[PDB]
Image: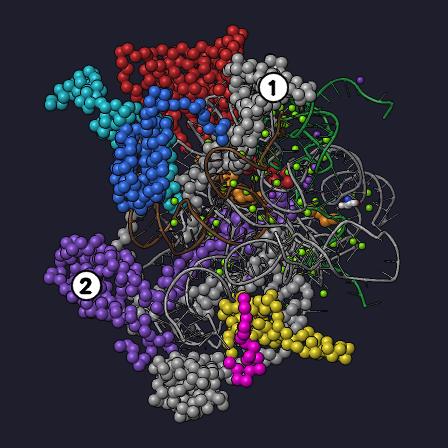
Chain colours: A blue, B red, D yellow, E purple, F cyan, I orange, K brown, L green
Amino acid sequence: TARGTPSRFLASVLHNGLGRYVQQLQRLSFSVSRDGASSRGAREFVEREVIDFARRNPGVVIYVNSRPCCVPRVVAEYLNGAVREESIHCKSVEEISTLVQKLADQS
Amino acid sequence: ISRKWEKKNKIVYPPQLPGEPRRPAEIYHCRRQIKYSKDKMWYLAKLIRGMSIDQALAQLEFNDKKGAKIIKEVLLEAQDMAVRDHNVEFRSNLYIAESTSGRGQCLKRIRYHGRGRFGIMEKVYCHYFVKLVEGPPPPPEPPKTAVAHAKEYIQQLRSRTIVHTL
Amino acid sequence: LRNRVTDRYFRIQEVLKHARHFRGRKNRCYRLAVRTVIRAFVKCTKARYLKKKNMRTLWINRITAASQEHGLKYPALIGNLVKCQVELNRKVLADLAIYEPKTFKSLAALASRRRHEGFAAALGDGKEPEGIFSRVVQYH
Amino acid sequence: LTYFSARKGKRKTVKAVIDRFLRLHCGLWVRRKAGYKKKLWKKTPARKKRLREFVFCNKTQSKLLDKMTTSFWKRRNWYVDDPYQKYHDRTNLKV
Amino acid sequence: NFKRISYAKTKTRAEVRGGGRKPWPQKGTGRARHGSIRSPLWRGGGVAHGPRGPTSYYYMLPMKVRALGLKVALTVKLAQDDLHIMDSLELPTGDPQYLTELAHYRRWGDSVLLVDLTHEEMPQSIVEATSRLKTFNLIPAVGLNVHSMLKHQTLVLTLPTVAFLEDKLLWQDSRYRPLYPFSLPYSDFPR
Amino acid sequence: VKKGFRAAFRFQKELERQRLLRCPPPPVRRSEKPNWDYHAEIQAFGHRLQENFSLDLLKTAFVNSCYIKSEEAKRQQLGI
Amino acid sequence: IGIRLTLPPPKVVDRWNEKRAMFGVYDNIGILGNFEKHPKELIRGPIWLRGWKGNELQRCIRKRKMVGSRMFADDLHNLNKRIRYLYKHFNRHGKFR
Amino acid sequence: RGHKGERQRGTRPRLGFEGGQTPFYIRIPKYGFNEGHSFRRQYKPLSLNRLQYLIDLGRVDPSQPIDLTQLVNGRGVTIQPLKRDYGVQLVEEGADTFTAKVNIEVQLASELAIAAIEKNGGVVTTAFYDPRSLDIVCKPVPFFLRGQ
Amino acid sequence: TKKRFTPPIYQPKFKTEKEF
RNA sequence: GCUAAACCUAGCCCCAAACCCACUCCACCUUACUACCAGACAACCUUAGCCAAACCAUUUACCCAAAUAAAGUAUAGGCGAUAGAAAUUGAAACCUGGCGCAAUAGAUAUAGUACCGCAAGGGAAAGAUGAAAAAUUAUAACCAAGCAUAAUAUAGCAAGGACUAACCCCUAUACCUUCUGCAUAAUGAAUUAACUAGAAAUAACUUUGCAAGGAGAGCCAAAGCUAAGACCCCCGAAACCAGACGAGCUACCUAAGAACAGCUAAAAGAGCACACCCGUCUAUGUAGCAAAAUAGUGGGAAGAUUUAUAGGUAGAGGCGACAAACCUACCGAGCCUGGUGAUAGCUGGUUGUCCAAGAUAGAAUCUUAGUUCAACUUUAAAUUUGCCCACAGAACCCUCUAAAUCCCCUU
RNA sequence: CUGAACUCCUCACACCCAAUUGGACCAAUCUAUCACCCUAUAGAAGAACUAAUGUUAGUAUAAGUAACAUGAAAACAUUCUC
RNA sequence: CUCUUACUUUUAACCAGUGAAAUUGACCUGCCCGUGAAGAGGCGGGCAUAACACAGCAAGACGAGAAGACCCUAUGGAGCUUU
Ligand code: MET
Ligand SMILES: [K+]
Ligand SMILES: [K+]
Ligand SMILES: [K+]
Ligand SMILES: [K+]
Ligand SMILES: [K+]
Ligand SMILES: [K+]
Ligand SMILES: [K+]
Ligand SMILES: [K+]
Ligand SMILES: [K+]
Ligand SMILES: [K+]
Ligand SMILES: [K+]
Ligand SMILES: [K+]
Ligand SMILES: [Mg+2]
Ligand SMILES: [Mg+2]
Ligand SMILES: [Mg+2]
Ligand SMILES: [Mg+2]
Ligand SMILES: [Mg+2]
Ligand SMILES: [Mg+2]
Ligand SMILES: [Mg+2]
Ligand SMILES: [Mg+2]
Ligand SMILES: [Mg+2]
Ligand SMILES: [Mg+2]
Ligand SMILES: [Mg+2]
Ligand SMILES: [Mg+2]
Ligand SMILES: [Mg+2]
Ligand SMILES: [Mg+2]
Ligand SMILES: [Mg+2]
Ligand SMILES: [Mg+2]
Ligand SMILES: [Mg+2]
Ligand SMILES: [Mg+2]
Ligand SMILES: [Mg+2]
Ligand SMILES: [Mg+2]
Ligand SMILES: [Mg+2]
Ligand SMILES: [Mg+2]
Ligand SMILES: [Mg+2]
Ligand SMILES: [Mg+2]
Ligand SMILES: [Mg+2]
Ligand SMILES: [Mg+2]
Ligand SMILES: [Mg+2]
Ligand SMILES: [Mg+2]
Ligand SMILES: [Mg+2]
Ligand SMILES: [Mg+2]
Ligand SMILES: [Mg+2]
Ligand SMILES: [Mg+2]
Ligand SMILES: [Mg+2]
Ligand SMILES: [Mg+2]
Ligand SMILES: [Mg+2]
Ligand SMILES: [Mg+2]
Ligand SMILES: [Mg+2]
Ligand SMILES: [Mg+2]
Ligand SMILES: [Mg+2]
Ligand SMILES: [Mg+2]
Ligand SMILES: [Mg+2]
Ligand SMILES: [Mg+2]
Ligand SMILES: [Mg+2]
Ligand SMILES: [Mg+2]
Ligand SMILES: [Mg+2]
Ligand SMILES: [Mg+2]
Ligand SMILES: [Mg+2]
Ligand SMILES: [Mg+2]
Ligand SMILES: [Mg+2]
Ligand SMILES: [Mg+2]
Ligand SMILES: [Mg+2]
Ligand SMILES: [Mg+2]
Ligand SMILES: [Mg+2]
Ligand SMILES: [Mg+2]
Ligand SMILES: [Mg+2]
Ligand SMILES: [Mg+2]
Ligand SMILES: [Mg+2]
Ligand SMILES: [Mg+2]
Ligand SMILES: [Mg+2]
Ligand SMILES: [Mg+2]
Ligand SMILES: [Mg+2]
Ligand SMILES: [Mg+2]
Ligand SMILES: [Mg+2]
Ligand SMILES: [Mg+2]
Ligand SMILES: [Mg+2]
Ligand SMILES: [Mg+2]
Ligand SMILES: [Mg+2]
Ligand SMILES: [Mg+2]
Ligand SMILES: [Mg+2]
Ligand SMILES: [Mg+2]
Ligand SMILES: [Mg+2]
Ligand SMILES: [Mg+2]
Ligand SMILES: [Mg+2]
Ligand SMILES: [Mg+2]
Ligand SMILES: [Mg+2]
Ligand SMILES: [Mg+2]
Ligand SMILES: [Mg+2]
Ligand SMILES: [Mg+2]
Ligand SMILES: [Mg+2]
Ligand SMILES: [Mg+2]
């Protein structure tokens, strides 16, 4: 509910969009499994989608680390210092691409 | 059971820098398995809370409750423990920082009622915890004055905004 | 094969995390908390209808207060602004009353002028042209 | 009805159904009219002829008797000179 | 599942010790009414709906279905380059290290299933090598099964085994419905 | 003792989170944390601001006097 | 409470031991062996459950018929009562008639 | 399960019980529809279309005498002596298109079926088999394993 | 009506005899 | 911060295999565990009943020694419920295993012990360091309810919308069950942890195999047949029966004992009145001192008295100066065990998430607290009209010359 | 003029009936095979509790309430009161 | 009893020691009128309203206790009697 959760006023970071627009997403850290079945969609994203995504976002540094893991995750770090970790466990390539694009558009 | 209070006297702080302020000495002491009720022991623990080491002993010495002697004995051995072991210069330079009672392990016994019925009574036990901090006791908080009330009220009136608008 | 629930702790905490700010045993005892948490969620859903209802009532009260400062009643201001083909809603008018008093007085004067033009039209037999502010812009 | 017998663990057949009804292999059940041998002196010949007819059962009664009899009575029989042989199969039946 | 027997069993309220007498009178005690102390509601009572072992899960697929499963598994191995054909299973040496290196050199994967025509006529060289290995298993042609083929990455069949498999599997495609079990004598069976 | 591993594993992570809240670790440089490439981050710094920075000049901008003296001290301590 | 504070010891499963490596072997003994032996003859267990399946009532009836004379007096009494209860439950109680 | 009543508790009456009303399967008068059913002789029909079909595929050899053993061996008919079967009956179905000349031994044969066989020059004979011999003649191999 | 007397039920003695 | 929490073993379950077990000395059927004296006493004998038939009265499955099949067939039966063969048929059979439990589980079991009962009998609870305790200032911590650190400020199912702000403002009649309808002052619930409740045939449907054949003898077959998936709860009576155990309480009886001051009369089922026996009335007590008592007042107190000890009568019974008394605190007929998981159309309860369709004329019934068939509702499938309705049409007898209905193309 | 979850507006849409019925998913556990900071595809079953005057255990509430106890002095010898 | 009063003991209340039981959905637990499953601390309209102990009282919480013994129902029992 609203009473049981914190609240804030609408705002931006460094008055973003006033003088110029700066992409608030700063870093993406992917953790994919070479053999993990739950990382099948994550591997598909790396093979064909992350390379094109890096072209469209030169200001975002993307780290893809291939290590054994049961639940693949993507960590998004922003300029204001907020860190958000999202799971891509058993997600298709389209769902991962939508999730990654959602992280890029957030402040 | 838990015995974390006895382990709080084993913390060794790093040496202070020459410019750092003096750190008050903290002494933790307790007595386990006291044949007394924690509810009755709470009033005695509440009474001496915040008092100096000497004033607490004076109040407990002339108190008719049984736990007063037990608490006074705990303070006496805690006061000696501070000077002998915790490097406290003056034995009177202590005040009661924390003092409270806790439930201990109890034994259940049968109480016989009429008509062949019964009730289960417990042989109550309690723990007494005390913390001594070196230095004069902190002064009591002065009562809130009319100036403080008026200043707070005006601050409330100066912090209200136009709600549900731009 | 005997199966037992090994993660019942996490099931309980999903309900108790929403009751942490409650008062009494119903913030820590699941049997009592679950009934109140469900009611809290139901009240949250039903309050969205009242939030819209209360906001419009608040806007009407604020508009009525500002209208009376200019000697106009709320129905006169709202009705005549419609006749001027001005589609400002009550949310904007309430904002204009608080932060743009000079603009709101012009809106009040415009509604007052349109209100007077309606009175002249009613008294007139119809052999006179429409009021200057009574003209309606036709769209096709 | 005995769904699981105590000695074989199999469904049993209610023998009251067997002594009264004939099941054609098409799924129909044939019965005789109740009271066709009772008080014939007070019944008109038109009424008595209807009582002597061999009538069929409806869907509910046919389904009820299927549950009360085992699969032995639903098998296809090739009795020699069977009077009801021609009625065991349907002809020109739609839906 | 066809050869699985579950030995798990629990005692119902009629098999737990005691519980014959009603614990207290039906009315007047102020407590909930109970008729036995071994009821499933009670601590230490019987189990309402628990395992009633031993339980058998025996069922048989049609003979042609189980015969067809071998054909599908054999086809999958050939289609995925997981099937290899050998003239014989004889090895130059009985050292198991030779067989492991041979599979690695030919890229046979982690596990290899070796099938010979008959158990008695298995070469001694391959038997010694496979007995000391865990991922290399030697079975007779009669012992071929879907589970073993699926568990092992690579399937190895001898030329006599291939002819043996074709005769046995294709016999189901052009056979009459049985009048009696095929163990009994037939005019043209076996062979 | 209930059979299983996932429930015990899940509870361990909850305990680790609570321990961090009780005793927060001191903040450390993002470079010391994993997933850091200084050269990659420098290039993205210019691209976010839509500025054609010179890599030679931009890298020297983040080099402070205190860092150089500390780096020299470390080499002397290790005898390099 | 109700959940362990430490991880259980790790589960070490030898996927390639002799039992798992040779599981399923000879399941086609009838098909590939001139039908000399039925695959049901490979089942090892209770003598009243080799190549046979049934519900609880059918198992209790079959066990009493085959090894009822070899059972202990207390075990036989419980089996007899179980058949009586199962007879009443299956043939008299239930949602469907 | 429902709300109360015998439904939820599961104590509803037996199948066929109609709440105390005289049930349908009882109020109907008894008649001898199935009286003596277990003592009626049954004969598996064998149409000349079926017989001609077997010969054209080589499942039944017309150059040798045809009896119950040959019909079962060719999987032409299925005989169940335990189910009161007494052999096969040669029926007249497909007599128009029947052309093979065979020596067939059956248990029953209609007048038209006999004529169709004899038109092509074949011989048809009706022979009786008691239940013991019927099982032996249909499956000789199981009998020969009895040592009798 | 008949007398309705419910005799008291003594709990087992061991539950009130445990010691440290 | 306490209280606590956590654990992996003890062992156990179901099978296979294999046919177990008794005695150092001494004691032990009398009052068992008692060194040493006249016996002649000696075993056999249909189970019943709950329950099902919706009552109940005939009747109602209970290993009887080869898996399968014949077959749920012959047959039996208030020909109802239900019971149920045989001839014949003829297979496999390598103990050392586990999609069994892990301290409320698995045996009741650490133990038939503690404890309870006169007896038969009933019947528990629990443990947790480490390689080393001849390392005990050791093995850190965080986790239920309950508390403490830290009582409380107008107003209200205690929350929600919110808000600069905890409250103040606005909105809001806990939950389950049961009902025509419950905030209901109807039911259950102090709270926490653990435990605790949907078992299966008949067909049908869905998905494979093969196909006039299917199936690893039996069976089915006018596209069938084989295989799989998928539907059927928990607690509770008062009772009935069988076999044991009980007259150390009480009812009465048997053998052999004991008690009854003083006074009057001296004769006493006589009077006054202790011990003693009983329990009239009142108060107190009502989880009490007491599962029937205390205080006072009373009845009897040489008699049909009271009472100690041992014995007898046992539940289809005993015993009874009949109160339906009393028979081990609860006797319209004891208690324990077993049948027994008795039965209950009656009550209560019935455990994860999400969506969808969904309120229904009657008939019969020892039946109206329930069921079965219709009706209604649900799913799947087939193919063709369904609903709304234009004229024309549907009764005379009769006081309401009714609102309407039925039929019905078009649309 | 005010006034609904009616209707319109921006976006989205399977996302408000008891009994009952259909359907899509799924926690934990065991097993096959993967996986290897806790998962996947399947096969299995003692497979999920805010309620049964539910069972067992812990601890509250009533409640520090009801209730319970030791004649007096003294040298602890002794004496005194009843 | 008119018509009660005084004193003593016990209880009582306070201090110290020990320490039960039924009960308990959650309670942040007012009054009036009206309403409503027909008798409201919780709903509607008003009124009242800083917080928190202790001792009394018994009008209410349809107060606690005992799955009403009265009544009816059950094709539920049982004792007794009988042409
Ligand atoms: C009427 O008199 C009824 N209350 C019965 C009284 S005796 C239990
Ligand atoms: K136990
Ligand atoms: K049934
Ligand atoms: K309830
Ligand atoms: K009720
Ligand atoms: K009411
Ligand atoms: K009510
Ligand atoms: K009531
Ligand atoms: K007493
Ligand atoms: K006696
Ligand atoms: K009823
Ligand atoms: K006086
Ligand atoms: K009162
Ligand atoms: Mg207590
Ligand atoms: Mg049982
Ligand atoms: Mg029992
Ligand atoms: Mg009994
Ligand atoms: Mg109670
Ligand atoms: Mg019972
Ligand atoms: Mg148990
Ligand atoms: Mg119910
Ligand atoms: Mg009903
Ligand atoms: Mg039930
Ligand atoms: Mg019944
Ligand atoms: Mg002895
Ligand atoms: Mg009956
Ligand atoms: Mg009766
Ligand atoms: Mg008959
Ligand atoms: Mg009947
Ligand atoms: Mg146990
Ligand atoms: Mg043991
Ligand atoms: Mg806590
Ligand atoms: Mg309010
Ligand atoms: Mg309100
Ligand atoms: Mg009512
Ligand atoms: Mg209402
Ligand atoms: Mg109330
Ligand atoms: Mg209520
Ligand atoms: Mg009621
Ligand atoms: Mg309770
Ligand atoms: Mg089922
Ligand atoms: Mg089923
Ligand atoms: Mg109960
Ligand atoms: Mg009887
Ligand atoms: Mg008897
Ligand atoms: Mg006696
Ligand atoms: Mg005598
Ligand atoms: Mg005398
Ligand atoms: Mg006298
Ligand atoms: Mg006496
Ligand atoms: Mg007397
Ligand atoms: Mg006298
Ligand atoms: Mg006797
Ligand atoms: Mg007498
Ligand atoms: Mg009398
Ligand atoms: Mg009387
Ligand atoms: Mg008694
Ligand atoms: Mg029952
Ligand atoms: Mg009944
Ligand atoms: Mg709907
Ligand atoms: Mg009748
Ligand atoms: Mg009815
Ligand atoms: Mg119509
Ligand atoms: Mg029409
Ligand atoms: Mg509106
Ligand atoms: Mg809306
Ligand atoms: Mg919508
Ligand atoms: Mg999962
Ligand atoms: Mg799974
Ligand atoms: Mg369960
Ligand atoms: Mg729980
Ligand atoms: Mg409960
Ligand atoms: Mg207390
Ligand atoms: Mg006191
Ligand atoms: Mg009180
Ligand atoms: Mg007192
Ligand atoms: Mg006293
Ligand atoms: Mg005294
Ligand atoms: Mg008092
Ligand atoms: Mg209590
Ligand atoms: Mg209670
Ligand atoms: Mg308040
Ligand atoms: Mg208040
Ligand atoms: Mg009122
Ligand atoms: Mg009010
Ligand atoms: Mg008070
Ligand atoms: Mg009451
Ligand atoms: Mg009252
Ligand atoms: Mg009642
Ligand atoms: Mg009466
Ligand atoms: Mg009655
Ligand atoms: Mg009735
Ligand atoms: Mg009866």
On screen, G59 above or below A49? below
Q: Which residue is drawn at 40% across and 13% down?
A: B94
Foreground mark, 1 or 2? 1
Along the line of sight, which residue is nearer the eye, E188 or A23?
Answer: A23
Residue topped by disc 1: C131
Amino acid marked by disc 2: Ile
Q: Is residue B108 visible?
A: no
Q: Which residue is drawn at 39% across and 25% down?
A: B5
Region rendered in magenta = D78-95
Task: Measuring from the top left, give residue E20's x and y in whole percent.
Answer: 55, 55
Q: In which quarter of the image is residue H50?
A: bottom left
Q: Residue at x 32, y 71 (%)?
A: E173
Residue H69: in magenta span: no
Give left or right: position of L43 versus G60: right
Task: Measuring from the top left, give residue C136's x and y in whole percent.
Answer: 57, 24
The chain under label 1 reads C
How would you rate the neighbour count of disc 1 (Cα within 10 Å): few for under 14, some for 14-19, many for 20 or more?
Answer: some
SS at badge 2: strand
- Per the rendering, the mark at residue E85 is 2
Determine the residue located farthest toward the top in the rendered image: B147
Task: Measuring from the top left, give residue C60's x and y in whole percent.
Answer: 59, 22
Q: In which quarter of the image is residue F15?
A: top left
Amino acid marked by disc 1: Gly
* Mark 1–mark 2 distance (CA, rounded to whole Å): 104 Å
Along the line of sight, which residue is nearer the eye, B100 or H69?
Answer: H69
Residue D88: in magenta span: yes
Along the line of sight, which residue is nearer the eye, L1 or K28?
Answer: K28
Q: In which quarter of the image is residue K74?
A: top right
Task: Measuring from the top left, give residue D13's x and y in whole percent.
Answer: 56, 71
How many numbered marks, from 0 up?
Answer: 2
On screen, E74 above or below A40? below
